[PDB]
Amino acid sequence: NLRKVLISDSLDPCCRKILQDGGLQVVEKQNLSKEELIAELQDCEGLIVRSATKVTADVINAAEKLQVVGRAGTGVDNVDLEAATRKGILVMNTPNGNSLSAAELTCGMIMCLARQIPQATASMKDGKWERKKFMGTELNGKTLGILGLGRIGREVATRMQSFGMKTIGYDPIISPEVSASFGVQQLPLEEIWPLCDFITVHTPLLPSTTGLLNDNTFAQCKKGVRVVNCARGGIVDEGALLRALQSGQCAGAALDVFTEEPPRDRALVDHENVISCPHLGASTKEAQSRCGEEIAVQFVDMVKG
Amino acid sequence: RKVLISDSLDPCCRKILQDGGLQVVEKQNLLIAELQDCEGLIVRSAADVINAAEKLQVVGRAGTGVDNVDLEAATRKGILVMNTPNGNSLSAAELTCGMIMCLARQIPQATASMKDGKWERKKFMGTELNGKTLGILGLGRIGREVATRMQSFGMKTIGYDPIISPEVSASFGVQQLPLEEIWPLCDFITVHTPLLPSTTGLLNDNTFAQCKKGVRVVNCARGGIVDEGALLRALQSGQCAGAALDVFTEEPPRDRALVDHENVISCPHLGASTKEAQSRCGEEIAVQFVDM
Ligand SMILES: O=C1NC[C@@H](COc2cc3[nH]c(C(=O)N[C@H](CO)c4ccc(C(=O)O)cc4)cc3cc2Cl)O1
Ligand SMILES: O=C1NC[C@@H](COc2cc3[nH]c(C(=O)N[C@H](CO)c4ccc(C(=O)O)cc4)cc3cc2Cl)O1
Image (cartoon, rainbow over all chains, first blue to last red; front, side, top):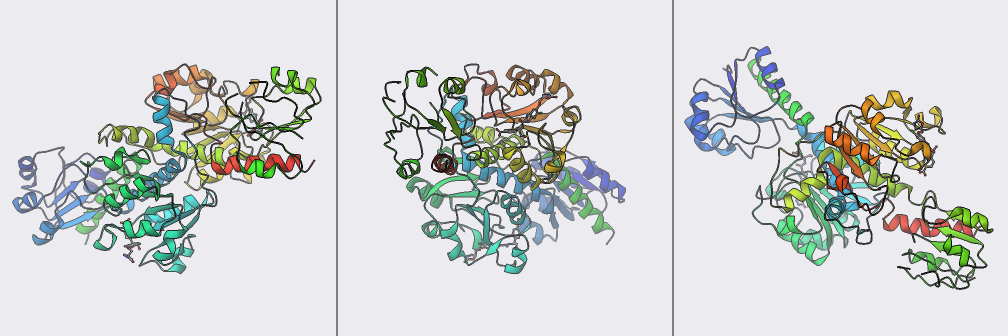
């Protein structure tokens, strides 16, 4: 059963600490090339990654002891889950660990869109004083649409409520009565689009949420809507967003995530009304430490049944 | 009733200034010949002015304070200066909150990186606000608005105001402490005071010396409350991890050392630059006038 675990990426020593406390032997490697990793996994039931180490069908297939792969983070981009499940290898991740960091970044993106803070800093650093060029928006009394009312969507809701934003939204699993208890009014999507000043997505990436925002939904929005995607690349159709930015149907967007990372296509990043980060939603010392801890705790519970 | 308007004003304010007499002409970029013979005045931004002026009763600035109109020359004549001290409050508080989130996650620096074709995930390791301490100096309209918003993020809000009682500030969840007890506790410090002798260099080498190593500071209030030489020294040592500045001792600033620092976020004094603030000030000034 589960004994010895390799850590192949850099995450807080709180991870190692909890693993050995629960009986597991631990080793701690870093970077490691496609050939390198497998020579460690010779003797290992367990592999903990962050984002850098790719766990492809190759490593999975070529590693003849590996029973579980743990990601100290959200989703499994860097783990071939098709090939893992084929070989009976359990894949786990730490969904709770990043919630607050992702919600805080989303709120900062909304403030940034409202007041053009990234654009203003760039203008100051270019030696300009362009007070006129900037006219921002007060959030108080504006409507924020929240698509997805799990962990992150509800944390975004309660913070933006403090700004006196009205928070409306939709989730197919969360009842209107439960969303009401954290101040989010659920309506049909067709009724959400024309009410929103700001839209933010907090859904998993599924067929049903791939291009959730598209040409059809932008057609239904108020002119000048502002969009945030701090969830997963492709929930917002990037073509449809660029078309909405060019027409003015969309007055601005804030993107932490892209269909391709890093993105080869530069048109959205380069747009004047787009502010962007290189997938920083989970990039806080606090989230990184909580994910380290959460994966270790998940591992030890599997040894104790 | 001839009324000049020496500033980019909200078009609501003219559509207002025809309840009572108001013969208006909104001429920006001015200079002094403009106000020929006019008795009752409105302004936004932009003395020698009123001295060569004639029959003028009330001057009104759609904004807070009067830092673009000589109050003593106006007191040298009969002239009452009105302003709209609540019109800009929410917009200034909202910008301050956005500056706090930008300092925590370096969103302006991340955007500049991305627009250079970079994908810099390690440089941009940030801080969670939940569980951090925000020090708020000045607990008037703006300070209390910043406090209740940042409490929703799980920040502990402490502060100091010589005029606001500890009971008033406890009612909006701000614990007042002596300044000496505030500095060592703060992860973030934000200033919401008037610019007075007592508040000029309120943050200086002596106060940075008592702060936590890595404190972040915001000034969306008035240029000079943060001593700019002291703030650059603190950024240079790492005593200050970052600063967000909407305001500068000289606007526009000719000393570029702070604006050019990698850990400084800056705006060209945008705290009151929203449609809603500019509309609310245009009308709060009317009700002060049109209800003597
Ligand atoms: O007409 C329609 N076209 C397609 C469909 C609209 O698609 C949606 C599908 C959705 N799915 C979910 C969803 O799975 N929500 C749960 C929470 O209940 C959840 C689980 C995990 C996470 C996370 O990983 O952070 C987030 C949310 C929300 C959501 C919203 C919308 Cl608008 O309806
Ligand atoms: O030991 C000392 N070191 C320095 C010295 C004084 O420091 C202070 C002086 C202060 N003055 C005030 C102040 O005038 N506050 C009132 C609110 O009651 C106020 C009025 C208008 C506005 C506004 O225009 O938005 C804001 C606030 C706050 C404050 C804080 C501090 Cl730390 O004492």
